[PDB]
Length: 430
DNA sequence: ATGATGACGCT
DNA sequence: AGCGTCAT
Ligand SMILES: Nc1ccn([C@@H]2O[C@H](COP(=O)(O)OP(=O)(O)OP(=O)(O)O)[C@@H](O)[C@@H]2O)c(=O)n1
Ligand SMILES: [Ca+2]
Ligand SMILES: [K+]
Image (cartoon, rainbow, N blue to C red; front, side):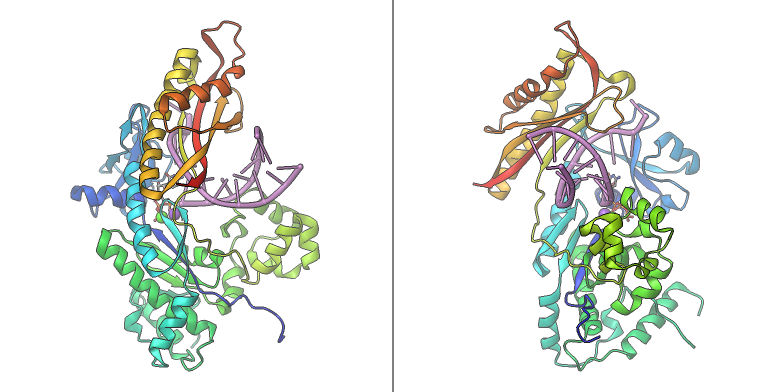
């Protein structure tokens, strides 16, 4: 009752760019705009691997991981943009720089947590409180929420998508208590107004469209963002959670998409997030551990406490290349040349990072895979990163992995290497 | 022969 | 430290 927390203390938004890599290429090349198109890397094996897909192309069944030769069988007019290749490997610099453009814009509105190349969480609690004061109780016009969906509405006693959307928005606004400044539903609505403004600024200043979710925590904001894509935003209120979760497959909630979520389903004999409410917290802790059990107990009620962490820059800077099947590295010369290739790209990115961001990495992580292992990584070793010098970094990487060579011959490498990875970590201010 | 990333938990 | 999970 009066002491039962409802997890309505914050306003959190998740902003996610639509078909990011595709939009980056379509901004650069206007011939790709408003067309079925995809982004592909490499080209020789089966036309290249598709890594991003425009919504027009998704209508034909094109998906990520598809070989482009196979995507062309579903969508013969599919247009393709190729990832840049430098020093023999895919180079994602264009997308990292486009990401910085977006993140710097969102940072004007609030402190962000950079979750990925194209996603950021925003804690809007303070900004909402401010905007509510600037209001002083005037109602919020539907005109301020032109691309907002209210999940769960319309409901109660038109056949077009936008008609639905407006009907739900009208019901939501008509029931709002704009007089109470601590009403959570009011706070979410003002949050959504701000997110409309943020999304308009991103589009105005970059050309890029995005979707967003607005709720009271990160999991609900992420789920919300996915409900109405592309180019729309969705508000998921605390009150909408019971119905939303009642048919929500457990795997759709962030962190439950893998083995843990599969075990929740199998051990408890359930399918949907809402079914978790019927277990005590101690029961869930007994099955899934103290941390996971408490998290599930709260999360299935719409409650989660993970803070939006103030972090706009990535914590690691890594360079990786696979050498699949027949191309696995079988000579010391090969291993050494590719370590140098990776190390040169890493040196370039590290020097740029140090000039831009006033920090220096202090640890170099080297990771390899040997032919035969089902695990993505077969060995990971660290060494000191004392100088931004590619030849030194590649020599140190070789020193820390060279005893993996089963070969009795000095020149050969066995088993051959199917993956090389160099990662700079443990940043210090400079 | 998906590939190239990136954050965080466990021991 | 080194490995694994989960995600873009
Ligand atoms: N396995 C994956 C995943 C992502 N990505 C990259 O991260 C970007 C954002 O990932 P995403 O949000 O999951 O997908 P999206 O392309 O933005 O499309 P949308 O968000 O559904 O509109 C993609 O554009 C790139 O394809 C990559 O490389 N491999
Ligand atoms: Ca996206
Ligand atoms: K994303």
